[PDB]
Picture 1 (cartoon, helix red, strand yellow):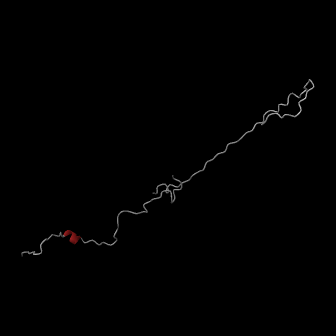
Picture 2 (cartoon, chains in turn blue, yellow):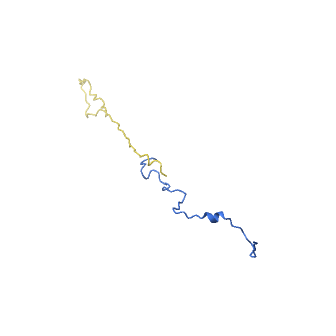
Picture 3 (tube, chains in turn cyan, green):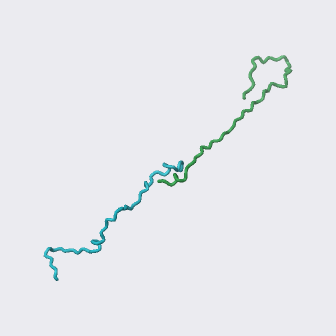
Length: 49
Length: 50
């Protein structure tokens, strides 16, 4: 029922919201994400040089 | 409008001598018609909200 088309004609709007958050300051650390981690089950590890 | 009244007495003496009848014909009533609009005026930006 289009009656006014000013403020209340189409109720249930999205409030001008988007589904993506913007971190204004860069806080990523590609170093660790690049260096892959390896699993160890035991606790008697040993490496050679 | 109506019918002719009774006029009460209705005696007669063998002769009418009327005035071409007392018909008093019907009355014409009339009536007029009007308009009803109820305008509506909406904006274009208010026709796309939720």
